[PDB]
Every structure is written in structure tokens, then in C-alpha cells.
Image (spheres, coloured by chain):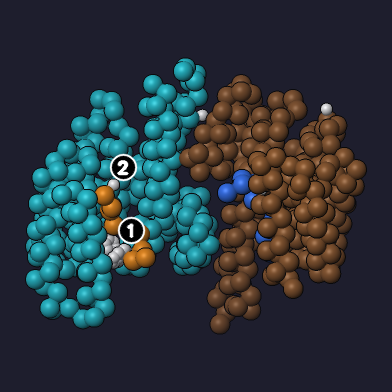
Chain colours: A cyan, B brown, C orange, D blue
Amino acid sequence: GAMGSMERASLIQKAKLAEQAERYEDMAAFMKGAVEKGEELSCEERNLLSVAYKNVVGGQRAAWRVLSSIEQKSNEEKGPEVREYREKVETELQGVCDTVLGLLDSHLIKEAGDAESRVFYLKMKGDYYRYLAEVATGDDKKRIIDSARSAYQEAMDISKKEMPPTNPIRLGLALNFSVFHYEIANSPEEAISLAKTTFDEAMADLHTLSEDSYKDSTLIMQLLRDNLTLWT
Amino acid sequence: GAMGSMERASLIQKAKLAEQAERYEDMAAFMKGAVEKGEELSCEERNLLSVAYKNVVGGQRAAWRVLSSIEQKSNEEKGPEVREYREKVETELQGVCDTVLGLLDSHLIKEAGDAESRVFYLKMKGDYYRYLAEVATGDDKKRIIDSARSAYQEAMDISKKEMPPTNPIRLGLALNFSVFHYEIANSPEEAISLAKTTFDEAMADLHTLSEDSYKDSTLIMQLLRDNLTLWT
Amino acid sequence: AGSIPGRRS
Amino acid sequence: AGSIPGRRS
Ligand SMILES: *Cc1ccc(S(=O)(=O)N2CCNc3ccccc32)cc1
Ligand SMILES: *Cc1ccc(S(=O)(=O)N2CCNc3ccccc32)cc1
Ligand SMILES: [Ca+2]
Ligand SMILES: [Ca+2]
Ligand SMILES: [Ca+2]
Ligand SMILES: [Ca+2]
Ligand SMILES: [Cl-]
Ligand SMILES: [Cl-]
């Protein structure tokens, strides 16, 4: 495509430079170009792809929330501008989510056979449908929510069969799916139960880990605990 | 142009919303559209224009500095990618500076007759030539530096004739011109002298000010003092 | 509530 | 060295 004339290795190198320069839109474009080369991604490359788009959509989500709050307060007649601009940001956000979902569907997920890669991509699929669900209101909102649920569920089923309970991808997946239950699916008890069981099963497997693996698993356990403290 | 079909007042309103949402590229596009309506800008509108572009170029400058530092360290052969990507960011930065300079030349400066508006725009002109000078290396670098100097100098001459020494635009102009002398023109003694004389003449006029004007003038005086502490 | 960050920081 | 910020903050 747009990056079609640049070497895969140069796109990866430039994505790393873009992250150091905090140029996340560039980073996402370089990683989209890398995915479109058609080869599978390594662990490090999957993290570059996720970092790039998570930062781009994260900024859009924060702007959408600011605008949505102003719009709800307005509803003196300020005219159509707040709604129009919220709609503009919302369309942009939806476009980025559609782009990421399109990369996952063409063809990252179908080529991912190892449990670590397949879980990583299905967790991303759940996350980008979740971001679509945060702004959805029309006839497809139920279907968008169900698409997030289904992706997270398939990732959970693989992770519980193929990864230890301290694996950081398994932990991050459970963290994000618990956020889905609380914030999207109106299922706070499911969210709390998932976070608690995940935390406790990870705690019981920490004894198997090296110092560096322990650091990763306990970092995500603390995120689970932080949500549990907020929710209880 | 691109915003040609949106009302001036809607562009201004959306620029204010974009700032609240930290969407500075949008903010700059809305303000470019407002300027292109052809009317003069009010004080508040001039500040929206400056905030928008100062934030956009400020992010580009920070990214260029990160990339330029990596490039200088590289000069193992990492291939052409660091230089190529620094060049990409540099071209983008130059393009934004050219856009702002084009708005000032067509036709903000020529229509600005009041000292406050004309000084504001000439200070901006000096600043965007200064940002061009930060990345310049070729046959035009001397001419770019001189263009910044000339704009700042004309602004200084008007400000000293028409504004009190505590006026915040006069103070910010002197602050920025002193940064020009230190960082661009290799004239640290001129930079120190300008900052000191500006600070002292403002101090001696604080007694004339209301509480709110005093707050503005002392805030910029502290910036002058912070630079003097760094430079001495 | 927080979701997973892109980097450990 | 610092130049003028876009807003007082
Ligand atoms: C979804 C997910 C979960 C973990 C990882 S990681 O590679 O183990 N890693 C990098 C991303 N953030 C993070 C936080 C805490 C501990 C480890 C990580 C990647 C993706
Ligand atoms: C270049 C310049 C200088 C002052 C101003 S201002 O409108 O007085 N104002 C807003 C921008 N930043 C600022 C810092 C301290 C005190 C006042 C201000 C605008 C533009
Ligand atoms: Ca495969
Ligand atoms: Ca006029
Ligand atoms: Ca949340
Ligand atoms: Ca500086
Ligand atoms: Cl809009
Ligand atoms: Cl490039």
C-alpha cells in the first residue's frame, strides 16, 4: 500500500524510532505497512503494532470523552458545533479501529498458530471492538458488544489450555476482558469474579518464575488489584 | 479552502473545543480556516491561532531533536533509515512553518495597524523563522536567520514606542528574541543583555498595574529570570 | 478502571 | 532556555 515501496526491516526500524520520538501516528503507519508485507510478526513486532495503535486510539478516546462530556452538558443552545465535532472525532476513531480489525482479519489471526500469537491478536480484536462499543449507539451496538465478547472468549479459552496462569498475555487478556465486563457489558460481578480468580491463580504460580518473569506477572497483578479496589 | 464551507464563528468555536480535547492539529486547521475568511482577528482569536501552531510545531521540534540526537550518535552503520525519518519529520515541520508564515504574509500583518496586533504577528513571524533556523543547514540558513532577526527587530521597535514595558506581548517578544540571540544567532551576551534590561524595566513599571496585570507581567519576568539563571 | 498499557511503564 | 508558552499555564 502506502508503505508498499519500503523494506519490511526499514518499516520496523522506523516504527521503533517513531516510538522514541513519540510520533505514534507515524508508528502505526509504519507497522500497518509492515503487517501488509504479509509475513507473520515476531513477539517484539506484535508489541510495536499494539503500542502504536493503542496510543493513537487512546488519544482519540480521551478526546471523544472530553467532547461527549461537553455535549451532554449542553443538552443554552450552542448550535450544532459540539455534536458535529464529537461526530468527527468519533468517525476518525471508528476508522482507526476498523483499520486494526482489518489487519487482524487480513490475515494476522488466521496465520497465527502458536498460542501466544493467536491469543495476542484475539485480545487485540476484543479491545478494538470494545473501543467501537464505547461510542456505539445505533442498530449495531449489541452486535459490536458481542463481537468483542466472542474474541475475548476465544482468547480466554486458548490461554487457559495453553499458557500458565502467570503468563503476561494471559493476565493482560483477563484484565482487559474484566474491563469489558464492567464498563461495556454491564456485568460488574463477572468483572470482579474474573479479576479475583485471575489474581489468585497467578499468585499461586509466582513460585515457578524467575526474577524477570515475576516482575512482569506482579505488575499486571497490581493492575488487577487496582481495578478490584476501584470496583469494591 | 478546506474549511471554506464552515462559518467563521463555527471554526472559532471548534478551535476552542479542539484545545480542550488536546487536538492541536485540528485546532490549527480550524484557525487556518478562520484566518482564511479574510477578516482581522481579535485578541482572543490571535491567541487561539498561536496556541494551535505553537503546540503542533512544538511537538515536531521535540521529535526532530530526538531523531537528530540518534542520527548524530549513529555518525555501526544503521543504514539510511534514521536520516530518512529525521528528514521526513523535518520536511513536515518546515511545511507547518511555511503555512504559518503564509498566513502572516497573506494577509494578517499587512492589515494589522494597532500596535498590539502588529507586534503579536511580527513576534510570530520571528518565531516561525527561528524554528526554520533550528533545522537549517544549506544555502539559505543565513537568510532564514536574518528573516527571524528582521521580524523580531521590527516588533521590538514598535513595542518600545507604543507599549509599556510591562505589556505581556512586549515581554514575550523580548523573551523570544533573547532566545533567538542565545540559541540561533550565537550572541549570548546580546541575549543576556536583552533579558536583563527587559526584566529591570518591567520591574520598575509594576507599580502601575492592577493585580491581574501584575500577575501576567511577573509570570513572564520569571521566565526571563529562569533563562538568565541558566545562561549565567 | 485500567486496561493493559502498551509498555511496562 | 524557555520561550513564551501558548497559555499562562
Ligand atoms: C496484552 C499484553 C500483555 C502483556 C504483554 S508483555 O509483552 O508481557 N508486556 C508488554 C506490554 N505491557 C506489559 C505490562 C506489564 C507486564 C508486561 C507487559 C503484551 C501484551
Ligand atoms: C507572545 C505573547 C505574550 C503574551 C501573551 S498573553 O495574551 O498576555 N498571555 C497568553 C499567552 N501566554 C502568556 C504567558 C504569561 C502571561 C500572559 C500570557 C500572548 C502572546
Ligand atoms: Ca503460522
Ligand atoms: Ca486593520
Ligand atoms: Ca476504563
Ligand atoms: Ca530553548
Ligand atoms: Cl467538525
Ligand atoms: Cl521515512
Residue at the spot x=73%, y=45% of the render?
B168
Residue B136 quadrant = bottom right
Residue A100 x %, y %: 35, 48
Residue at the spot x=30%, y=45% of the render?
A128
Q: Nearer the viewer, mark 1 or mark 2?
A: 1
Query: Which chain's residue wears label 2?
Result: A
Residue at the spot x=57%, y=43% of the render?
B25
Three-letter residue code for mark 1:
Pro
Q: Which residue is mark 2?
A: A131
Q: Residue furthest front?
A: B207
Looking at the image, is B1 positioned above or below residue A103?
above
Looking at the image, is A83 positioned above or below residue A161?
above
Q: What whole-number distance in Å separates the C-alpha atoms at marks 1 and 2?
A: 15 Å
Residue A146 x %, y %: 18, 38
B210 or A21: nearer the viewer = B210
- Left or right, B54 with respect to A20, comes to right
A189 or A99: nearer the viewer = A189
Looking at the image, is A56 positioned above or below residue A38?
above
Residue C5 — which label? 1
Residues tagged by mark 1 and mark 2 found on one chain of the structure:
no
Residue A165 quadrant = bottom left
Task: For residue B103, say whether it is visible.
Answer: yes
